[PDB]
C-alpha cells in the first residue's frame, strides 16, 4: 500500500497484455518461423501481394489484380488500411519483399490482438464501470475461437482490425456522448470537447477503410438514436448532444473515407465504392435530422399540435419510414444494396459448401447444439449470455441509455452470429464484455472486493466463505477458456512444405520467369469492366487448380491462377462456364481441353486433397446441386464379424456387427474424371498432359516407409488397410495418403475393366504439377488388319517414384494416330526412363521423341 493502487487496475492490464503475447506470439512461433516465414491461411497471403506491390509504388496502391482470376482479373476489396500499414511497417523495417517482408507482416495481427485490450476496456468503462472494464480487458486477451485464430502470429488478415476499430468506434462514440452529456452549447464542442466526436469519426472511417461492409456500423449507431427517441418517455438521454456527436462523427468519417471512395465502377457493399460514402454522409444528415426534431420537442411542438406523450416517437417513425423509404426512388442500386445486407438471401445454394455460411448453433445437418459456442468462446459465451440477461434488467430498472445501446450492438452481432459461422469474431468482444459485467456482480455481491479493499488494507464486514466461491466461479470462467485458447494458438496454418516447395519450384522453373516478377509489381489501372479477358503486355499463360490455392500460387509461385479464394473462376458444367470445377470434374479429355483452351491454361496443379476429400466439393460446384453430385460416389467398405475385405453396393447388404470405414468409396464416373486421371493415374491415359514435378510423399507415409517398401503392393496394402480400420474403430476417417491407396485398391478390384487404363497400388506425391502440351502426333499405317495400338512407357518422378504411362487408340482406315505428351530430353525432373514401346498386333517398335516435336506438335510417321 498504496501500491498496488492505483496500479492494481493497471497491472492486470499489463498482465493481460503479457498473456496475449504468450498466446499470439510465443505459442505459434515455431510454426510460423519455420523453413520460411509461414503466413497462415489463404487471405493473409494476398496482402503479402498487395503490400509488396504498394511498397514498390508508394504511396499508390492497386485496385484491380489481373494477376489472379486468369485471364480476367478480379477487383481488390481488401482495404487500404492494412495495405498501407503493412507497407509502412515494411519500408521502416527496411524489408520490401520475400521472407524479409513476411517476417514483419506476421507481427501485425498479433499486435492488433494485444492492442485490442484497450478499446474493450474503454467501451466497457463507458457503459459500466472501471472494475468491470478491467475484467473485460483481461478476458479479451484469452478468448479463443476465430478471434484468436485470426489474431495469431502470421495470420495477417483484415479480420482482427474489424473488431478492433468497431469496438473502438462504439467506445469512442459513447465516450463522446458521455463527455458532452449535460454540457450545453456553447461549452461543447470548443476544441477540447471536439476531440471526442472527431476521434469517434476517425475510428468509424478507419473501420470502413479496412472493411467494405464496415458501413454497417452507421445504421447501428442510427439504431441507437432511433430507440433513444421513440422511447423518450421510457429512457432518459441528452438527444441534443446525442444527435450533435452523431452528425460530427459520421461527417468526419465520411470526410476520411472520401479519398478512397472511388475505386470501384458502380455501387457495392464489399468494394470501395461511393456507396459507403453515401451511407456515412446520409446518416450524418439523418443524425442532423434527429437534432431539429428534438429541438422542436423542447418548445413543445408535439404538445401544441396535440400529439401528447407519443408525439416525438410517432414523429421519428414516419421520419424514418420516410428518408430511408424514399431511398428506393433514386438511385437503387443504393436501396437494393442496403437491403442486400438485411434480406439474407439464403438458403445456400449451392454449390455451398462453402464452409462458413453454415449457421452457428446448428451442427451441419441439422440439429441444435452449443458446441460451436464452446469451441469458439470457451466459458465466456455462457457467462456472456447470462451477463446480457442481467443487463437486460438493469435497463428495465434503471433505464440507462448507453446500456441500451450496448444491448442493441449485442443483439445485432448475435443475429449475424446466428446466421453464419463466418462471423464468430464479432461476438468475442460481446462475450468478453458481458461476462465481465456478469463476474463484476458476482465479485461485488460475493464480497471479494472485500477483501481486496480491506485486504490491503482496511477492515470490512465480509464472509471468507463467499470470497472462496467468487474465486471458484472466476475459475470456471477463466480455465476452460484459456485451456481452449492455449491449444488453439499452439498451431499455425498456412501451406504445408509440400505446397511451398512445389510452388517455389514453379516460380523458378517456368517460362517468362522474369516477366511475371516485373508484372507482379506494376501499378495496374482500373478497368470499367472485367468480363472481357485482360490485354496482357506479354504472352501470359494460366495456371489452373482448385480455388483454395489461388493466393498461394500467386504469392509464392508468382504465376497466374485461373481461380482464386475469392470464389472466382470456379466455373461449372450445368452451364459450361470454363473454370476449375468444370475442368477437374470433366468427364472426357476433350471437355477438359475445351475449358483449358478457353482460359489459355498451360500448367495444372493438383494435390491429394483435390483427389479425395475436396473432390466432392468440386463436383457440387460443377453439377450445381448436391443430389446431382451423388452420382460421383457409390458404396462403402466394410469388415464383417469374421474380419473380411468387404464392399456392399447397397447400404442394406452390410453384415450385422460389421465394422465399416467412414469413407465413401467413389463411383465409376469418378475414375472417369480429370482429377483422378491426373492424380490417381499420375497423368496416364492422357494426350496433352505430362507430369513435371512431385512433392514428397504425404506426411505420414514418408514416416511409414521408414520400415516399408513402397513398390511391394502386398506390403503397402497391409498397413493401408491396417490403418484404415484401427482408425475406423473410432469415428475417424483414415489419413488422406491412405485414402488414395484404397481409391486405387477399389478401382482395381471393381471398376477397372479387363484392362481399362490400369494403375499401380502405391502412395504418390502430396502435390503434382502437369504441363499442358500439344503432344507429338504419331500416325502411320498399321499391319492390316489390327484393332488397337497400345503405347506404354515407364516414367520416373523427382521422388525416385516410377509408374507407367499408357494410351490406346481406335484404329480406323488402317492408320492409327496417337498424341504423346511426355518427352525425353526435357529439363523437367520428371522424365520417362524408357522409350514408347508401341504395339499393333504381334509387331512392335520403339520410338524416342524430343520436345521440339512434342511441344510444337510435329507429326511423326510410323508404319508396320
Ligand atoms: Mn479473411
Image (tube, rainbow, N blue to C red):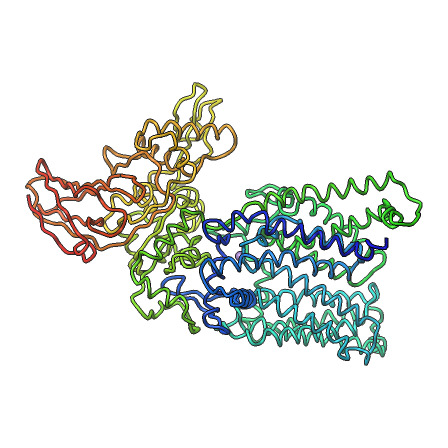
Does residue 473 appear in this view?
Answer: yes
Task: Please give left or right for residue 376 compared with residue 501 in the image.
Answer: right
Quarter holding residue 864:
top left
Q: How many numbered badges does the structure rendering display?
A: 0
Horizontal and vertical percent for residue 361? Answer: 62, 46
Q: Residue at x 61, y 53 (%)?
A: 147
- In the depicted view, which residue is nearer to us: 708 or 367? 708
Task: Using the image as rendered, state which of residue 153 and residue 598 is in the foreground.
Answer: 153
Asked if 749 appears above or below 605 in the picture, the reply is: above
Q: Residue at x 37, y 60 (%)?
A: 560
Residue 93 place in picture, x, y as percent:
53, 64
Residue 613 position within the rendered picture, expressed as x and y whole percent measured from the top left: 43, 42
Residue at x-position 53% and y-position 70%: 272
Between 330 and 110, which is closer to the camera in this rendering?
A: 110
User: Which residue is nearer to you in this view: 304 or 137?
Assistant: 137
Question: In the picture provided, is 202 more to the left or to the right than 92?
Answer: right
Q: Can see residue 573?
A: no
Residue 309 falls in image quadrant: bottom right
Question: Is 443 placed above or below 653 here?
Answer: below
> How far from the left and from the top, in percent, is residue 223?
70, 65
Amino acid at each position: 500500500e498504496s501500491w498496488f493502487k492505483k496500479y492494481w487496475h493497471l497491472s492486470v492490464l499489463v498482465i493481460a497484455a503479457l498473456i496475449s503475447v504468450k498466446l499470439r506470439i510465443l505459442n505459434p512461433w515455431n510454426s510460423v518461423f519455420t523453413w520460411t516465414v509461414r503466413l497462415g491461411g489463404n487471405d493473409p497471403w494476398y496482402y503479402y501481394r498487395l503490400i509488396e506491390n504498394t511498397i514498390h509504388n508508394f504511396p499508390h496502391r492497386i485496385w484491380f489484380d489481373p494477376f489472379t482470376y486468369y485471364p480476367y482479373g478480379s477487383y481488390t476489396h481488401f482495404g487500404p488500411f492494412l495495405v498501407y500499414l503493412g507497407s509502412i511497417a515494411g519500408i521502416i523495417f527496411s524489408a520490401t519483399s520475400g521472407e524479409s517482408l513476411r517476417a514483419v507482416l506476421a507481427f501485425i495481427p498479433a499486435i492488433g490482438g494485444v492492442l485490442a485490450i484497450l478499446p474493450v476496456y474503454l467501451l466497457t468503462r463507458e457503459v459500466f464501470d472501471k472494475r468491470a472494464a478491467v475484467i473485460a480487458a483481461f478476458l479479451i486477451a484469452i478468448v479463443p475461437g476465430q478471434f484468436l485464430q485470426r489474431s495469431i502470429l502470421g495470420f495477417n488478415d483484415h479480420h482482427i482490425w474489424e473488431a478492433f476499430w468497431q469496438v473502438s468506434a462504439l467506445g469512442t462514440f459513447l465516450l463522446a456522448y458521455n463527455r458532452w452529456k449535460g454540457h450545453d452549447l456553447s461549452h461543447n464542442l470548443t476544441a477540447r470537447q471536439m476531440a471526442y466526436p472527431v476521434i469517434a469519426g476517425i475510428t468509424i472511417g478507419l473501420y470502413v477503410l479496412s472493411w467494405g461492409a464496415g458501413f454497417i456500423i452507421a445504421p447501428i449507431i442510427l439504431a441507437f438514436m432511433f430507440f433513444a427517441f421513440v422511447l423518450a418517455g421510457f429512457v432518459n438521454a441528452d438527444r441534443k448532444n446525442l444527435s450533435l456527436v452523431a452528425v460530427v462523427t459520421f461527417a468526419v468519417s465520411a470526410l476520411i473515407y472520401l479519398p478512397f471512395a472511388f475505386n470501384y465502377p458502380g455501387f457495392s457493399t464489399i468494394f470501395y465504392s461511393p456507396f459507403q460514402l453515401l451511407v456515412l454522409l446520409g446518416s450524418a444528415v439523418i443524425a442532423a435530422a434527429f437534432y431539429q426534431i428534438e429541438k422542436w420537442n423542447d418548445v413543445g411542438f408535439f404538445e401544441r399540435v396535440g400529439l401528447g406523450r407519443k408525439g416525438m416517437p410517432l414523429a421519428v417513425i414516419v421520419l424514418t419510414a420516410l428518408i430511408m423509404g424514399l431511398f428506393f426512388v433514386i438511385s437503387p442500386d443504393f436501396a437494393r444494396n442496403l437491403l442486400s445486407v438485411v434480406r439474407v438471401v439464403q438458403p445456400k445454394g449451392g454449390a455451398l459448401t462453402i464452409a462458413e455460411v453454415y449457421p452457428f448453433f446448428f451442427t451441419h445437418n441439422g440439429e441444435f447444439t452449443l458446441t460451436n459456442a464452446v469451441l469458439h468462446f470457451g466459458a465466456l459465451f455462457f457467462f456472456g449470455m447470462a451477463g446480457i440477461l442481467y443487463s437486460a434488467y438493469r435497463f428495465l430498472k434503471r433505464r440507462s441509455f448507453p446500456e441500451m445501446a450496448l444491448l442493441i450492438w449485442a443483439i445485432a452481432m448475435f443475429i449475424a452470429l446466428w446466421g453464419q459461422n463466418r462471423f464468430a469474431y464479432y461476438f468475442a468482444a460481446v462475450s468478453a464484455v458481458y461476462s465481465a459485467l456478469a463476474l463484476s456482480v458476482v465479485f461485488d455481491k460475493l464480497h471479494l472486493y472485500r477483501a481486496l479493499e480491506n485486504a490491503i488494507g482496511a477492515r470490512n464486514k465480509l464472509s471468507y466463505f463467499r470470497v472462496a466461491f467468487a474465486l471458484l466461479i472466476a475459475l470456471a470462467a477463466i480455465y476452460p477458456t484459456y485451456i481452449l485458447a492455449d491449444a488453439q494458438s499452439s498451431y499455425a496454418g498456412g501451406p504445408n512444405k509440400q505446397w511451398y516447395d512445389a510452388l517455389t519450384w514453379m516460380r523458378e522453373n517456368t517460362p517468362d520467369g522474369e516477366k511475371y516478377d516485373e508484372y507482379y509489381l506494376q501499378l495496374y489501372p482500373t478497368p470499367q469492366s472485367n468480363k472481357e479477358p485482360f490485354s496482357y503486355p506479354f504472352e501470359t499463360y494460366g495456371v489452373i487448380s482448385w480455388w483454395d490455392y489461388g493466393h498461394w500460387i500467386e504469392a509464392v509461385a508468382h504465376r497466374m491462377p485461373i481461380a482464386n479464394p475469392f470464389q472466382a473462376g470456379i466455373g461449372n458444367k450445368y452451364n459450361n462456364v470454363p473454370g476449375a470445377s468444370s475442368f477437374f470434374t470433366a468427364e472426357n479429355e476433350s471437355y477438359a481441353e475445351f475449358v483449358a483452351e478457353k482460359l489459355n491454361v498451360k500448367y495444372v496443379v493438383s494435390d491429394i486433397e483435390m483427389e479425395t476429400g475436396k473432390y466432392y466439393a468440386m463436383a457440387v460446384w460443377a453439377e450445381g446441386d448436391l443430389p446431382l453430385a451423388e452420382k460421383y460416389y457409390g458404396g462403402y467398405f466394410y469388415y464383417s464379424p469374421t474380419g473380411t475385405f468387404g464392399y456392399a453396393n447397397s447400404q442394406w447388404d452390410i453384415p450385422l456387427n460389421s465394422i465399416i470405414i467412414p469413407l465413401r468409396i467413389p463411383s465409376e464416373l469418378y475414375y472417369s474424371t480429370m482429377e483422378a486421371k491426373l492424380h490417381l493415374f499420375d497423368g496416364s491415359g492422357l494426350s496433352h498432359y505430362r507430369m513435371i514435378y512431385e512433392s514428397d510423399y504425404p506426411a505420414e507415409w514418408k514416416s511409414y516407409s521408414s520400415q516399408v517398401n513402397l513398390n511391394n503392393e502386398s506390403q503397402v496394402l497391409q498397413t493401408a488397410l491396417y490403418e484404415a480400420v484401427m482408425r475406423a474403430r473410432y469415428g475417424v476417417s483414415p489419413t488422406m495418403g491412405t485414402q488414395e491407396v484404397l481409391y486405387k485398391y477399389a478401382y482395381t478390384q471393381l471398376y477397372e475393366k479387363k484392362m481399362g487404363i490400369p494403375v499401380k497400388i502405391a502412395p504418390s506425391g502430396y502435390v503434382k504439377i502437369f504441363e499442358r502440351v500439344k503432344g507429338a502426333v504419331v500416325t502411320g499405317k498399321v499391319s492390316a488388319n489390327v484393332t488397337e495400338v497400345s503405347v506404354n512407357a515407364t516414367i520416373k518422378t523427382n521422388q525416385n517414384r516410377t509408374f507407367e504411362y499408357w494410351q490406346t487408340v481406335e484404329v480406323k482406315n488402317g492408320t492409327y494416330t496417337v498424341v504423346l505428351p511426355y518427352s525425353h530430353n526435357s529439363d523437367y525432373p520428371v522424365k520417362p526412363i524408357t522409350p514408347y514401346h508401341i504395339k499393333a498386333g504381334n509387331v512392335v517398335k520403339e520410338i524416342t521423341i524430343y520436345e521440339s516435336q512434342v511441344q510444337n506438335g510435329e507429326i511423326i510417321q510410323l508404319d508396320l
